[PDB]
Amino acid sequence: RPTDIKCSESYQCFPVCKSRFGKTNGRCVNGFCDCF
Image 1 (cartoon, one colour):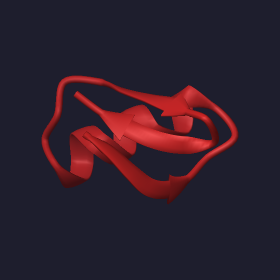
Image 2 (image 1 turned 90 degrees about the vertical axis):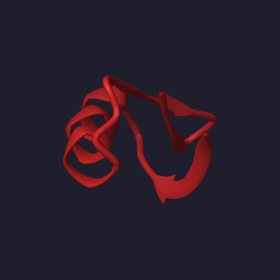
Image 3 (image 1 turned 60 degrees about the vertical axis):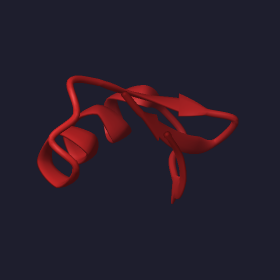
């Protein structure tokens, strides 16, 4: 899902998603993290 976690770049999200939600990967969509 998309979130409201602000980011400039994807490598910011990926570990945050893996840490928080336990998702496989994340990507910065339109300046906000999307985890999947």
